[PDB]
Image (tube, rainbow over all chains, first blue to last red; front, top):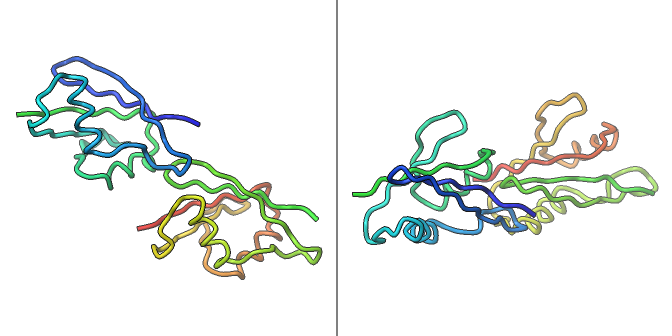
Length: 88
Length: 88
């Protein structure tokens, strides 16, 4: 009955919020619902371009592009996800 | 007159349901009755390919392909069966 901890950080300020999962198994938001969620935390202009990059299990710097790779984060089995913002 | 606990897990969310046996000794469903049963739990597109892999007694990742290997799960004498989905 549990959520995934997501920690983001832009301009050297770490934040954290939680994302519920369905009974089904997929994460209960999408990129369109995520990009506007990050713009809430940082008082960012939402029209700006967002370059979101997580960390893999085995430490690469992967890119986030679609709701298909948001599916992969569940199967990746990571303890908490960490997402870097690059704007402008 | 008793059932086998099967636990499935796709997108990192565990589920569980039970499967009865006959008086005779075989499991009381088959793959076509199983594959469409898993698609009920996960709201999966049933037209997608399913690659179902159980765990052996001695811990291998065996493949499930047919109703001949579903027979073997009874004789395998496992405490509860665990079935991983790989789609796409």
